[PDB]
Amino acid sequence: GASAETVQDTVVQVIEQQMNGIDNLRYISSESNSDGSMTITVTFEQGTDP
Amino acid sequence: LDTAKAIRQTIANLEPFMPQGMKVVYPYDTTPVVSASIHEVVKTLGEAIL
Amino acid sequence: KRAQMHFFSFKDAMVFAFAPPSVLELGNATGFDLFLQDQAGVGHEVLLQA
Amino acid sequence: VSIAWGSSYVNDFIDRGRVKRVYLQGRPDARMNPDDLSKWYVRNDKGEM
Image 1 (tube, rainbow over the protein chains, first blue to last red):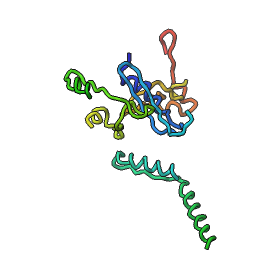
Image 2 (image 1 turned 135 degrees about the vertical axis):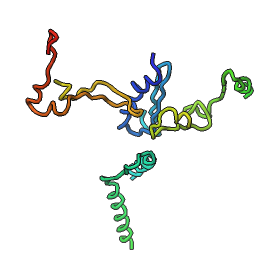
Image 3 (image 1 turned 90 degrees about the vertical axis):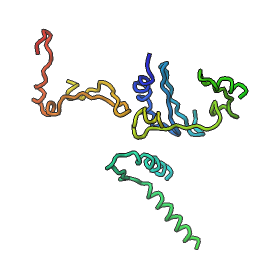
Image 4 (image 1 turned 90 degrees about the horizontal axis):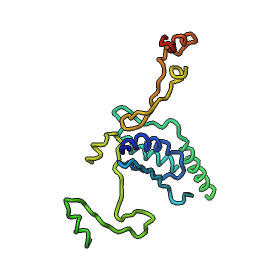
């Protein structure tokens, strides 16, 4: 039952701000949606142990 | 040397959004001693050969 | 494309059907990729126009 | 006791596009000295103070 905006500022942004102090972190992205879902994708450098 | 470089590079991109009267300064920074060490020893090295 | 013209030519709804790249591990989709950001904190309107 | 002196965190709030916190701490002059705390009155069961 949440709007993109609700998922982005209540959940998707409270997480992103902690996404640091992680090794070989190349880049981070995310999505927030009407259906209420969201996903953060933390992509790493070649050679990281998954 | 790569790291200090990269950050300087990340701010260079961010400075151009900063307000009217703020400048970025680098108070502490040990990067230089690294380059000084390698420049010296490298130099002696070559005196050793002559 | 022998099906791309079929609907992509609709005011009703875009129906862009496409094929996956050479190696799937990276994509679903060929060509290029990028994100336009918001470093000024202009807010949603500008970036949307940009 | 732990809201005026011990700035209590209550919830978030968007600030120019970034979630930040909202602290609730009594005024500075009402947590400075030992008798400066006698100022803080509580509620009374029977409505009183």
